[PDB]
Amino acid sequence: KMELPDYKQWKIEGTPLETVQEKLAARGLRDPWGRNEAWRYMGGFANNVSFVGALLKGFKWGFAAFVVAIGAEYYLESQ
Amino acid sequence: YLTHQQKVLRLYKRALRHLESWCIHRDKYRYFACLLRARFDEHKNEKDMVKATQLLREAEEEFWHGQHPQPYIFPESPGGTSYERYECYKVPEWCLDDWHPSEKAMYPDYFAKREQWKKLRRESWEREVKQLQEETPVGGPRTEALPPARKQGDLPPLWWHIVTRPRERPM
Amino acid sequence: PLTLEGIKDRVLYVLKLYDKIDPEKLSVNSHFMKDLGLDSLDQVEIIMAMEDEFGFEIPDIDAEKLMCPQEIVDYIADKKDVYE
Amino acid sequence: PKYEASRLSSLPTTLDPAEYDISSETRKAQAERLAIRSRLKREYQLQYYDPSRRGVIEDPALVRWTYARSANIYPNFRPNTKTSLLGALFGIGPLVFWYYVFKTDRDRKEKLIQEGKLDRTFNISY
Amino acid sequence: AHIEPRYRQFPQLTRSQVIQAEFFSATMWFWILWRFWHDSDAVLGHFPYPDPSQWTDEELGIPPDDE
Amino acid sequence: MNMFSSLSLVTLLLLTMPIMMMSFNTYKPSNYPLYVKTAISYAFITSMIPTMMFIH
Amino acid sequence: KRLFIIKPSGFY
Amino acid sequence: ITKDMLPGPYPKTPEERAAAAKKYNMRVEDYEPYPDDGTGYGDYPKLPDRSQQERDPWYDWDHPDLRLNWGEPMHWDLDMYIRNRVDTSPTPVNWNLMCKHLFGFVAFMLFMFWVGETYPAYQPVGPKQYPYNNLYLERGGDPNKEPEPVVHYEI
Amino acid sequence: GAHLARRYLGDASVEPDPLRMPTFPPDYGFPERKEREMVATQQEMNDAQLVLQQRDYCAHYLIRFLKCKRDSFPNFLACKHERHDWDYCEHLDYVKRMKEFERERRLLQRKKRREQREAD
Amino acid sequence: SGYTPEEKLRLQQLRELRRRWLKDQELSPREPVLPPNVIYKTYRHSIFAFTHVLIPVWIIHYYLKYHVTTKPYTIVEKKPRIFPGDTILETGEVIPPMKEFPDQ
Amino acid sequence: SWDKDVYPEPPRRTPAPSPQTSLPNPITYLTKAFDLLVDRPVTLVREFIERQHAKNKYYYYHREFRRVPDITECQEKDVLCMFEAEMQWRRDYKVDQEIVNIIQERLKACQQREGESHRQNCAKELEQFTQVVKAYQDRYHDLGAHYSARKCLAKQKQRMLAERKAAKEA
Amino acid sequence: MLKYIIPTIMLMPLTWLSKNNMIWVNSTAHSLLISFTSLLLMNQFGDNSLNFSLLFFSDSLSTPLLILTMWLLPLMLMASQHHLSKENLTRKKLFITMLISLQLFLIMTFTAMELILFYILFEATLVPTLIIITRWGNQTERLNAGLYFLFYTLAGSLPLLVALIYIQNTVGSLNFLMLQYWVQPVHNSWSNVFMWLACMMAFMVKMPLYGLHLWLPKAHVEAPIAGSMVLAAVLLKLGGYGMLRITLILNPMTDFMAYPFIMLSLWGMIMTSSICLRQTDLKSLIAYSSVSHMALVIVAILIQTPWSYMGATALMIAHGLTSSMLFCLANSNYERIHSRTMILARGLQTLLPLMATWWLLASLTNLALPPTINLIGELFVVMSTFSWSNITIILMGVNMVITALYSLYMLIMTQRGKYTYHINNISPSFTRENALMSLHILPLLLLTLNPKIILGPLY
Ligand SMILES: CCCCCCCCCCCCO[C@@H]1O[C@H](CO)[C@@H](O[C@H]2O[C@H](CO)[C@@H](O)[C@H](O)[C@H]2O)[C@H](O)[C@H]1O
Ligand SMILES: CCCCCCCCCCCCO[C@@H]1O[C@H](CO)[C@@H](O[C@H]2O[C@H](CO)[C@@H](O)[C@H](O)[C@H]2O)[C@H](O)[C@H]1O
Ligand SMILES: CCCCCCCCCCCCO[C@@H]1O[C@H](CO)[C@@H](O[C@H]2O[C@H](CO)[C@@H](O)[C@H](O)[C@H]2O)[C@H](O)[C@H]1O
Ligand SMILES: CCCCCCCCCCCCO[C@@H]1O[C@H](CO)[C@@H](O[C@H]2O[C@H](CO)[C@@H](O)[C@H](O)[C@H]2O)[C@H](O)[C@H]1O
Ligand SMILES: CCCCCCCCCCCCO[C@@H]1O[C@H](CO)[C@@H](O[C@H]2O[C@H](CO)[C@@H](O)[C@H](O)[C@H]2O)[C@H](O)[C@H]1O
Ligand SMILES: *C(=O)CCCCCCCCCCCCC
């Protein structure tokens, strides 16, 4: 009915879970549930914007339309 | 009424949940969940029970000091935001006996099957009572545990209100 | 909309992502203590992982009795009115 | 910093010194407490699950509670120093307090009206 | 349904929701920029605030100490 | 005046109509929520007319 | 599938 | 219910205490009546003054909403301790400390509002000036009288 | 703020009292001081139904703005020039109130400085 | 900590019954046995406007015109603002303009 | 419909449309639509109803009460005279309540009509309200729930006694 | 009044000569017809009351009380016929005869011209009421409730008889129209203080005044449903009607004699409102709610202002429908679970949806939601007591808060939460019960459209 993605693909390498495993390794400890969290750091969840990037969503096209809108205004006031 | 082991394991689970409430981020929680497991592991083999009780006693005082004043609660757990939310939709099964005949006529097949469940309940009651009588000590039951059906063709005593209870999402 | 097999698949999925369990020696009937060599602190963590997986709490009185994957599946199927 | 219990904030069980002094006498007491609860639970369940029962399972505990909260009070009342002082202070005291508050207020208002110093310019509804 | 749930993966998205969200985010930024181009006084100050310490004693009618 | 006052009262009266229909006169529970939602949207339009006259 | 909804009688 | 199964007077003798405990379905060691002042408690048990919120929510209570079992003795103030009313649950902060901080915060704010009232902020301007003798007629002044002129000069 | 520190922390005897100013005669140091002119008549502001707080020495600009707003409906983006004129008149009115505060402040300072002459 | 054999058996037996009960809540195909584009979007909106705007506004206007406004002070309007330079419809009066402003 | 002297209204001064925009006024077209869709059909229905009323003209009357001797002319305990004087006083009391209500309605109408200039422009109405409330208070205030002509007369005589005393000593 | 007295009397032969199975149909149908004709009493004049004869008169105070009285008889018959089903025929007809006789005494009581005639019918109401409580109540405590009810009433009423006979000797008449004109002021003396007390205490006990109210929670908890309805709806208002009339001849002594009773009432209403928050018996809670509401009426009557007398009249009528409706609501639960304990049956909204709606509407009128006539009456008393003394707003406002809390506590406890698991005999609401609730609430809310008819003579 539902197909679960293959479980072997969930690896902690390349994620901040790897950093934690190294901090715990220094002390002699190990994190046995790391792979159970890996999915949160992979795939479409891998890169998320910073807070400034969130506020600036749509700024590129808003700014583009602004320049055209004011460029047209200067053109009209020129005539 | 809880053994020493039960108390220690309940403290471990409770402390991990409050720890997760403080950490929030999964990687951070994994780091401190391992450090916390190490502390419980450092005294796992303590044998002098007087010493172990003192450790548990002190650990509960440390937990009280460091608990989250607003820990995460699963939504449907007691005190959660969805706790008891659907109780207003849970209607007991006996209400169906009072339906008007024209209401029952809308579900002929459901009510035929319901009539078989009531027949099963009626035919089984006297054996259920008898089994409880002959399995209960003279003074009375000393725990709330109930037995299973012994003979084939018997039903576990006092089953109706467990089996026919409302669904968790009744609508 | 859970099913009996969907619950089993996810219960075993979580256990296969636990480093203390050999994913090949894991069956629905494995006893966490007699068959897998875990202890009672490991058992608490397994139960906590199941609560996170399915998003609901298993009280300590009930949790302490679930000692194999199949019992976890049976417990979850019972609380969620899953009959298929 | 130790927990300080109050009337409206009980002492947590995990911090109770007696929750760890579970002796053979206390374990015996707990078993007896569970025995009563199980005995009552069985009595209730035999009626609750009875397929031929339609009605209300009367609870003597509930009957005793509502009876204790009304009918049983006067028979066990004794007029002594305690009940007389509370009766006098709480029953008579407020009536005297409010009599003087209103009597004083009304005497003042009446005196002002009788001297034309209370402003009733537009007061024609009473 | 038209959007099927996924297990441990980023959800399925539609074009309509992505484009509509972007258009309204861009409209917010166009509007702020357009409004600030014409109405910066509403943010920075409509009128100059004078320096009272630089008014002469003549215009304030302050007589000299010997009067 | 007559349009301003009439429309301001029709806004309020429009909002009560779905309540009165719950007296089963002309009642179609098929989509009561859509009926109520539509009544609000129409009331919003009728309330803008006297608002415009006040602004003017 | 569709499940019967236990309600009190609404006829009366 | 027979009269022997209803609350009675305060128990005087140990046999009465053992009988009262039985009637209330309690251990004679757990049974303790209210003090025998003239307040009318009789032999009704004195139970712990705890809210029903404090009871285990995972136990299979006969009355889950009340967290009561059938036949167990009800607290005298049960109706005050239902989960909709008085909660006695333990708090993360001590009750006494909680009162000090709430009262202290309120007292500080009230003090500072008196201070800010005695030393108001304002701008360095003179009064607003109005024409026509400070709008004497518009403010309702009597037309038949004459206000002292209010004159405003340029600056 | 600056003025508030001087009065509340510094010497309050040489700072204006906002609730009692002016305290010097309007012609003190001001030979032949003209009167403020009022362009709008009382009857004009009565028919315009100006809010009483709006019936000040800038009311003629407010009346002109209000008329434009009505006449330009539904174009609610017109009358910006008229709005600015009323706003500007109010700005000058405010600056005049700022000068009154500064005039009083300097006179109070002069008085104290003079009352040191009469005892030094 | 684990189910006793007797607890395991009872849970297994109750589990069978509960699942049979839940399966019995499913409706059969015939249940319930009930006793006996753009243009169509204009119609509903057209009939709705007629029965919920036009008819109510006919009733209100009739009520206001011929009952409410035939009684004193039932509908009282703030009198219109009159600005300098206006013309009165009732009389033809012309309000004079304001004085000449100083330049600013 | 109603007497304008009893319920006065100042003459209405509406400005003429003086647009300074090229955009059409949405209200003007809406005004025209309202007169066509709402006013005209409503007027036709009323005109039909007025036709039926014109066929069946009949009259009702405002009851007139002759004056009878008031309580001051009644002998003590003479219930037959006191009864007619008391009934007349009760009727006059109800009338005076409505006189105050008319004056209050005038005052409230003026306040709304005059807008922001109401404080200056409703002085005459506020004066008349002030005077009538004073007269009504003198007649009827403080009589109690069991009021009567006898108690009202007692109140007046007390007031006349005070006014005589003040006048004499002055 | 003969057009009402005689048809009321005819209900007795009607009930006794009916076929065995038609006693409820016939008595209910014709008592409803009598109620219909009662609307003819609305012919009231601005100045004069409606003075039929030397015995009977009706004014704006007695008219709404009459219409409430004649409306309640059919409602009482509907409410009673279920719990009386197993009673033998002759004893049913006797029960209906007591209800008819109570209506006969009541309509004559509210229209009697002469105060001594009023006294006799005022006192005759005790007999059928006492019989109804002690013969047809269910519990042992009904015998004690009858005695408390009887002797509390007679303790105050016998002094009233002496005072009234003394007044007739001194004045020469007890005719109320005569007293309006021959009344003389009451001077300060110890003789007049006790004359004042004898004239008022009988009515205070019936209201009941706080401190003399202990009989009332007994009488309700023990009375059958019809006894509770007329006790709450009408019989309490005998006291209010009595004071509204007799205070005419007690001025100006009421200026200061009222103080002890205003204090008892102002404080009493808060005490009895607080008591409702901890009541375990649903019928006892509703009974204590009546004490709190009638405390306002006592205050309103005692301060004697046009606004307070109008509020007192509206309050008496509004409380009559609300309180009687609440008893009927509580009784409908009692007929299923056979217990008055409030906490026994919970979550009933899940099981009886439409009945829960009647519970909500009765609660909202009890807490005086505007613009119900419950609120109109209470507000008018609040307005007039504020003029009496501004500080009363503190007590009146606090009582409004407490009234909401117990009104909704009763609603939440019984209707909401989870249903009791073992109570499995909650059968669907009968048509009879639903019709009974609507015949309370519908006229109550319809009166909001025309409040003047229940505002009394001072309107
Ligand atoms: C008077 C003018 C009023 C304002 C008018 C403003 C008009 C602006 C229209 C913007 C339409 C943009 O449309 C949307 O843009 C974003 C830009 O990141 C694209 O998004 C693109 O970058 C993001 C990451 O940064 C990812 O989703 C992906 O790499 C790509 O899709 C969308 O695929 C496209 O659908
Ligand atoms: C922008 C916000 C503007 C408003 C800011 C308001 C801040 C004012 C805070 C006032 C409250 C201070 O209240 C004060 O807290 C401290 C900290 O525990 C208490 O301190 C005391 O209790 C603690 C803990 O029991 C112990 O260390 C010791 O007994 C003592 O230090 C004081 O007994 C209490 O009086
Ligand atoms: C000279 C003065 C004498 C005055 C006498 C005036 C009344 C005379 C009445 C005579 C008839 C009495 O009628 C006798 O009693 C009752 C009432 O009708 C009848 O039987 C009754 O049964 C039930 C009540 O139990 C009812 O349906 C109904 O009241 C009637 O049918 C008897 O079958 C009849 O025999
Ligand atoms: C709320 C509804 C109540 C329903 C009550 C049902 C019972 C109805 C009883 C009807 C009684 C009618 O009683 C009779 O009516 C007729 C009208 O034809 C009146 O007839 C008279 O009325 C007036 C009297 O001033 C005159 O116009 C004229 O003398 C004559 O028309 C009689 O004076 C009256 O005796
Ligand atoms: C719930 C309980 C309610 C209790 C209410 C108690 C009210 C008490 C009212 C006190 C006023 C009684 O009435 C008052 O009695 C005194 C006597 O003492 C009378 O006094 C009379 O005889 C004395 C002689 O001693 C003369 O001096 C005096 O001139 C004369 O008036 C007054 O005429 C009267 O004003
Ligand atoms: C100068 O133009 C005035 C601007 C107002 C500044 C506000 C200063 C806030 C200081 C805190 C208040 C403390 C109470 C005395």
Image (cartoon, helix red, strand yellow):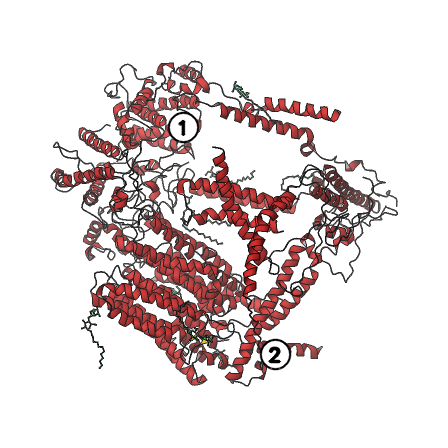
User: Label 2 crowding class (10 Å Cα cut-off): few <14, some 14-19, many 20+?
Assistant: few
- The residue to which callout 2 is attached is K157
Visible residue check, residue D99? no
Camera-nearest residue between L445 and J28: J28
Assign a secondary structure to mark 2.
Answer: helix
The chain holding disc 1 is B
Q: Is residue A59 left or right of residue L368?
A: right
Visible residue check, residue B138? yes
The answer to whether mark 1 is within 8 Å of ligand 2 is: no
The kind of residue tagged 2 is Lys
The kind of residue tagged 1 is Leu
Q: Residue at x 69, y 30 (%)?
A: E38
Camera-nearest residue between J97 and K159: J97
- The residue to which callout 1 is attached is B19
- Kindly indicate the quadrant of the structure image that contains residue B59: top left
Camera-nearest residue between B109 and L170: B109
Camera-nearest residue between J75 and D94: J75
